Amino acid sequence: DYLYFTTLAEAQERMYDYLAQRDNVSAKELKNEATQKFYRDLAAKEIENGGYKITTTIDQKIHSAMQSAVADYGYLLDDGTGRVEVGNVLMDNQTGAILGFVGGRNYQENQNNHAFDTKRSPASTTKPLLAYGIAIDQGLMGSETILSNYPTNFANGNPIMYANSKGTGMMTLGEALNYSWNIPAYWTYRMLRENGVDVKGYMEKMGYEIPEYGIESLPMGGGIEVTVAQHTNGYQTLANNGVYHQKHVISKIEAADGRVVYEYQDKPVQVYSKATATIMQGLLREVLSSRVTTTFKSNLTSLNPTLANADWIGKTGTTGQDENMWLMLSTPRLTLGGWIGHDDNHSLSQQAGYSNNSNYMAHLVNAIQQASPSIWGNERFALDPSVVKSEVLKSTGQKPGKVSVEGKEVEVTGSTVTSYWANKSGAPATSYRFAIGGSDADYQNAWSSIVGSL
Ligand SMILES: *C(=O)[C@@H](NC(=O)[C@H](C)NC(=O)CCCCCN=[N+]=[N-])[C@@H](C)O
Ligand SMILES: [Cl-]
Ligand SMILES: [Cl-]
Ligand SMILES: [Cl-]
Ligand SMILES: [Cl-]
Ligand SMILES: [Cl-]
Ligand SMILES: [Cl-]
Ligand SMILES: [Cl-]
Ligand SMILES: [Cl-]
Ligand SMILES: [Cl-]
Ligand SMILES: [Cl-]
Ligand SMILES: [Cl-]
Ligand SMILES: [Cl-]
Ligand SMILES: [Cl-]
Ligand SMILES: [Cl-]
Ligand SMILES: [Cl-]
Ligand SMILES: [Cl-]
Ligand SMILES: [Cl-]
Ligand SMILES: [Cl-]
Ligand SMILES: [Cl-]
Ligand SMILES: [Cl-]
Ligand SMILES: [Cl-]
Ligand SMILES: [Cl-]
Ligand SMILES: [Cl-]
Ligand SMILES: [Cl-]
Ligand SMILES: [Cl-]
């Protein structure tokens, strides 16, 4: 089944590297297609005939439970657009070890591996990693920062849409994330581009391959296509307080006599500051609790109320024509990535991600917990001590003070909130352009409202 061929494919690649090095084949010689073909064939025959011991990270009980879960509850994905395919990867946050996965609805009927082989746009699940997470990390926004959701156009003149909405007005980062509003994400990424932030540095530290970093819709999944395993690794990084561990299924390959052919080497990388990662955890907790873009917390509370009280965080994504839905879930211990879609890329139903995938993944998480009762853990995500707490105006997301509004020096006061920052000084004093993005006209409208409240 999926585990047999995924493991075999990975073992063959590791055996290929080992045999080429054993036989002293040069980097140049390895560029020869006929030489590569011979070493791939030799690697396959070595595994087939060689009596090697392959040690995997797979938890057999959990992986078996996940197979039974998709066999029993995969039909919950069928939304009237034909048989819906699925991929899931369960990853240990502290190691990057893959404990189990779902390759698809039924290997016997369709062998395509939707966990490791299929690449699709991760849509709005890109936003925490590539837009908001980097902006917080660079000290360009805090947890209660205000962003523009005022109407604006892409470079080609097309309006930035959210369902049938051309946008609203100013909103908090929390509102922007809970709803997955697009314009705030667009402005956040535009700010990173304008400031010359090395976004590629962050994304490549987590193993992402993105060909063009200038794509305006990168936060909404434009110009990015990922496997479920790779994208699970991005969420692993945020859940693990910003420390990436490279995903793996193979831990070790030994000859019969115990000679080590290959052994996974942990190379932990602090991709985001502990402050950034823990602030993002708090925001993604509210994405699930708000239930705006996913019913997951309602589904899970019914199936397993004790498990629903674990510290779940996560994020949804939907591609433009509903071809792909994503739900990424973490507790402190584990991350579970989930994709659904069609092999031929045709549209799912409008609510496929919101309801069907959420219900299926609640069943999958419950199946995992029944197989391994302690595996999700009862630990909480918590702000790192390095987080800076700033008292800011709810209205501006910046500290109270004086601003020039249409000539007149205005004393900006009102309701305050604690905003979490990952810099040294926390939130700046309120300035006229207090929000991420927005036009002159937007700011005239926003300030008119705020002044009206003093
Ligand atoms: C995150 O997943 C977000 N999804 C998107 O932004 C998605 C990639 N595209 C859209 O929702 C807008 C494209 C639709 C065509 C434009 N309308 N016209 N004409 C959120 C929204 O789920
Ligand atoms: Cl399998
Ligand atoms: Cl496979
Ligand atoms: Cl040999
Ligand atoms: Cl096991
Ligand atoms: Cl896609
Ligand atoms: Cl515009
Ligand atoms: Cl909200
Ligand atoms: Cl970049
Ligand atoms: Cl990638
Ligand atoms: Cl670039
Ligand atoms: Cl591996
Ligand atoms: Cl041997
Ligand atoms: Cl840190
Ligand atoms: Cl909740
Ligand atoms: Cl609900
Ligand atoms: Cl979404
Ligand atoms: Cl689509
Ligand atoms: Cl199909
Ligand atoms: Cl705890
Ligand atoms: Cl906390
Ligand atoms: Cl503080
Ligand atoms: Cl303060
Ligand atoms: Cl600072
Ligand atoms: Cl800005
Ligand atoms: Cl304007």
Image (cartoon, rainbow, N blue to C red):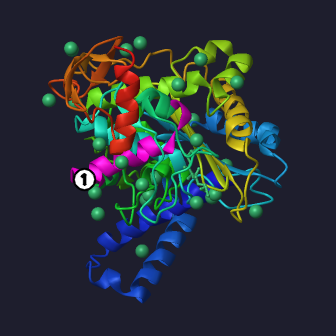
Residue ID at (59%, 52%): 115
Q: Which residues are magenta?
A: 178-199
Residue ID at (63%, 45%): 163
Question: In the rendered structure, does residue 180 fall within the stretch colored magenta?
Answer: yes
Pick the residue in front: 390 or 129: 390
Q: Is residue 403 above or below residue 91?
A: above
Question: Looking at the picture, how far across and down is residue 335, in whole percent?
Answer: 50, 34
Horizontal relation, residue 234 to residue 167: left or right: left
Number of disc labels: 1
Which residue is at the far front?
407
Question: Looking at the picture, how far across and down is residue 83, in whole percent?
Answer: 81, 53
- The chief SS type of the magenta part is helix
Q: Quadrant of ligand 5?
A: top right
Q: Is residue 36 above or below residue 80?
A: below
Kind of residue sitting beneath label 1: Glu
Horizontal relation, residue 131 to residue 43: left or right: left
In the image, the residue with mark 1 has its CB under 8 Å from the nearest atom of ligand 25:
yes
Residue ID at (40%, 85%): 35
